[PDB]
Amino acid sequence: SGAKLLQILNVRVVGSGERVVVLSHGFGTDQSAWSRVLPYLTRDHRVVLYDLVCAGSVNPDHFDFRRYDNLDAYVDDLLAILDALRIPRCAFVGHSVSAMIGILASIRRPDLFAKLVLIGASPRFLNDSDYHGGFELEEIQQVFDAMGANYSAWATGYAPLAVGADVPAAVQEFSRTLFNMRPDISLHVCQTVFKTDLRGVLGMVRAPCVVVQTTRDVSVPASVAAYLKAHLGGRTTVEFLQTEGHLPHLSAPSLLAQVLRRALARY
Image (cartoon, rainbow, N blue to C red; front, side):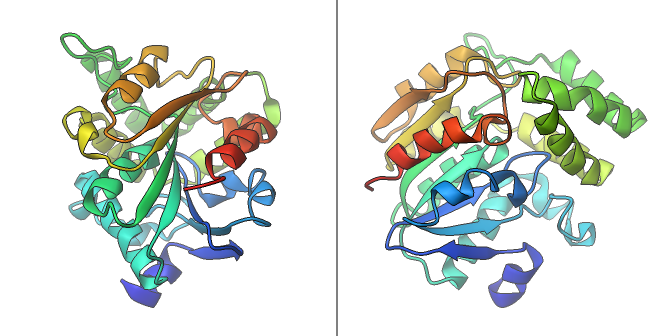
């Protein structure tokens, strides 16, 4: 907690304004993934950036495998950062696992989260009886095996699929941070995400929410955005980016920045 947590998770506060925005990165990146959208926000907003404890840019000996076996422990870190910074109200932009973290955080502390922007967002990745999440159990078992048997080969193959569009600089950048993650931590985060099911709690979210949908995301079927819009408890809209990929902040930052400026205008 406190100043030590601000140090350990590389917390940075840039820009200025009464509109505070937290940018929270996803699996396989760190806060540098926001570097190209950041200049579109800092004239108008006070921006809080931090690294998840699993990021390769954080000393991996801080990663407590027992503590971080659920997403609520990541929520605890986020809340402790905002409390240490004395921030009473903010908008939160979360990618991937951070979209799940933001949902949970907005339920824990509805006073603190005035708006959510969710990128690469899903409440559940595994398929269920009448629910298409995009993944089967046997498929993820093989992914987990590949991550353990040869993490470098797995990451080399995953990076272009996650970026989706043929944007070589974005593949190189995502690869860099993926290869920066300790393989056991990377596997553990993925296992934690795949066992999370937020469907039942979506109606507890009170904050307005913008769900950013790209034209294809290897981890998020197109139908998930409509599910989130139907079930999130706040005023929710889906904003459609005119390109593909799981990491639009890396592959199409100027387009994503348009959505962010609109979504962060008033809250």
